[PDB]
Image (cartoon, coloured by chain):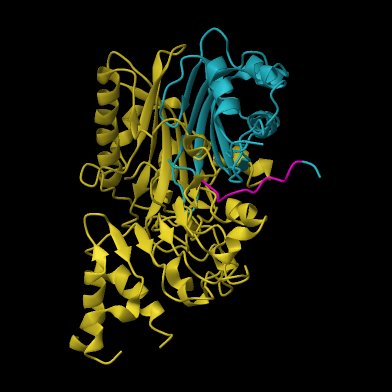
Amino acid sequence: SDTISFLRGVLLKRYDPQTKLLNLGALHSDPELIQKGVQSKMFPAMMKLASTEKSLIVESVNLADNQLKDISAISTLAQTFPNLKNLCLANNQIFRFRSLEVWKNKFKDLRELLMTNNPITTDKLYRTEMLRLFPKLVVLDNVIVRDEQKLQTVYSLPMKIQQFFFENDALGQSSTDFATNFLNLWDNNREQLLNLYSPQSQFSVSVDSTIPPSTVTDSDQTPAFGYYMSSSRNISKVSSEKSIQQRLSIGQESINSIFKTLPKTKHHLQEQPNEYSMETISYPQINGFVITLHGFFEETGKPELESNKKTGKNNYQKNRRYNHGYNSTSNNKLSKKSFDRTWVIVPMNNSVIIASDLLTVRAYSTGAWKT
Amino acid sequence: MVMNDANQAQITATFTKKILAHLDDPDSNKLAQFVQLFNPNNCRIIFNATPFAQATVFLQMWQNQVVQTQHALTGVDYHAIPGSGTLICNVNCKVRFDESGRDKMGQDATVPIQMNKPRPLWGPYFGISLQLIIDDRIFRNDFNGVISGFNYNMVYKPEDSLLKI
């Protein structure tokens, strides 16, 4: 609206585009504000507007010469600019630390700070607090306190994550041709894939039940692995060995027995395809190759056979067990889930056949190879 | 001959928990031991999708420019390939790095121009999905040159971690 628009206007004047710096000092001296006539409460306001402007990127902030004695007034700085990198609050009369402790391990990207003429500078302990408050700081009071790179040699491994890898173009590209053939048939028709499976081939399902941290972008905090926990073969999760001997499936009939238990999927592969990092690597002694794939799929359908209706809860009246009324991991809904799949294929003159098939399903989460 | 017995399955669980321990030790003199498990003649590591020709050089990497780590198993499963005499195991685990600000040797970033060692401060959890290729002699209680494949890759990461991937 027009009434708030002036507060938006003053930020434009006090932000310098080319130098990428936002000078905030002497707020009350804005000539455009005087025609209104003018407290101690406006400081949180801007900060909210700065995030929602969506047109200016700030990475340096000057806030000296504002007449402050306590830092609680600006505590909302960490909530708007986590990647701020150059703060100047010099020429102030702060003298204690309880109001500055609010930024513990925050402003990690910040690596330059000017706090000249402050009373804190005379203390002997002056060096110690920052050294933990801002681990990546390098320059303080225009004097070097850390050896730049020496820093950026610890906090960063010496290469960059690659989303695809393969020894040769002929081998690598052929695997993608296999993967496209394998996955598109997977969603549409389960019956045809038997011809790629040997009587010696073995298949298993592994389920990871860990909850991804909340800091991961687009993290799934309510996973639902209901249909997979009757067929999951996890060594460290279940200790009932007897069950593990039954989870493993060998042969043509056994593999398709599982294939109907799992719900129908549909991947946005060759469309959205930045997501599906895959590596393939040779298998010398058996003259085969190993294809490891990481990605996600959409459970668009439900399994035809429940496997818990023809034999499960055979006694009538009484329902199953933990009342799937939201209980347990939380249910058996239908929803997006990530997966890690590895392959072992032995080539043949007629056609390739799959030796082993491992499938690992986990809660949905973003990839690390993103940009 | 699809061999599948519970006795063999137990050995796989402890062996995977054993290899991770060597990767987690900030020691340096003991590091020569972990080399013996890797195959000296032919071996094919892969760490975050960059190939390493030699296994020995990849271990001096883990001690020189990599901070202390602390893994945490969550899921393991395996499959024995008939005729091959080798088996493949799928491993999932978490990862923490010491974000205190010094490396394994114990040298800080501040330049010297002039109580014991502080306890390390750990960071957020990461995500790992590890595939490795082993032969079947591990069942026979011998661990010399038994590792032939090692695909250590990560699938997700948090934004709060100081490490840049």
> For this view, does A261 lie left or right of residue A183?
right
Image x and y of residue A274, in percent? 27, 42
Viewer-closest of A220 and B95: B95
**In the picture, which chain is cyan?**
B
Relative depth, front residue between A12 and A202: A12
Q: Which residues are magenta?
A: B117-126
Q: Quadrant of the C terminus of chain A?
A: top left
Magenta residue check for B13:
no
Q: Residue at x 35, y 55 (%)?
A: A299
Query: Camera-side residue: A74 or A155?
Result: A74
**Residue name at image x 55 percent, y 53 percent:** A210
Asked which quadrant contains residue A194, the reply is top left
Compare residues A307 and A167 and report the one nearer the observer: A167
Task: Determine the main secondary structure of the stretch shown in magenta.
Answer: loop
State whether residue B99 is above or below residue A125. Answer: above
Q: Residue at x 29, y 26 (%)?
A: A175
Q: Quadrant of the N terminus of chain A?
A: bottom left
Q: Vertically, is A137 above or below B26?
A: below
Which x, y percent locates residue A247?
56, 41
Q: Is residue A291 left or right of residue B27?
A: left
| Relative side of B25 to B161, left or right | right
Which colour represents chain A?
yellow
Q: Residue furthest top?
A: B41
A143 displayed left or right of A267: right
- What x and y, as percent, mark residue A99? 58, 72
